Image (cartoon, rainbow, N blue to C red; front, side, top):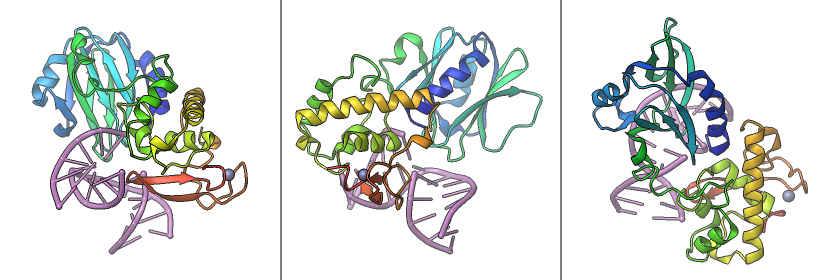
Length: 259
DNA sequence: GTAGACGTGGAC
DNA sequence: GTCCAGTCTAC
Ligand SMILES: [Zn+2]
């Protein structure tokens, strides 16, 4: 998931867990636990703490407890669900947080790529993986100036620039491809070749795209212009949508609308 | 940067 | 059977 999908998870999950106290933490795939390294220590420190809140930073979820903050990245297929501790678990459940009321928060991840870091609240934003993240796209911190500063300083493609979480946090393959189309810019061109008018236009479309996506609860898939539409006619000009590889990933675009 | 890594499963 | 699908990393 990207910012919109993670933001949607944050909103619906919060009311289901706020105020609940942790009684036990069970881990079925240790690799997911990154800090502390020892999964036994990870489990023991959260016992007895109550969930006080849930925030998002980039594509990360930040569970706020009493003293600690649990930082979770879903990567490609991680997902959360709340259910009764009396029912059988679903396939690929790797971590489970059991509460004192008999309910539990389950974490599933088919590909096992997700990660979890636990730090004291005051240290979380200063340690990895949150430490070097760029500004939030829906905040005053992100502006054309910030984009320009990083753009006019590299030779890599504009898609690579946008996928770099240190530049701006939250964009992935789907929204980078969609933002570039709406702004009318080819994904493979040098980030340093973009004019001042283009950068402003891109900033405008990035904010609007991510904003509309959050409103629709993420993929909004019915409002996609290019992602996954290769071979189909452009919604704006009718030219067949094409797909290639840019910055080591599948990239979708319209050869006429984007220049 | 442009591929391959890290587990697992669906499309063709 | 076999190519494709968020960060890291090493030829
Ligand atoms: Zn078009």
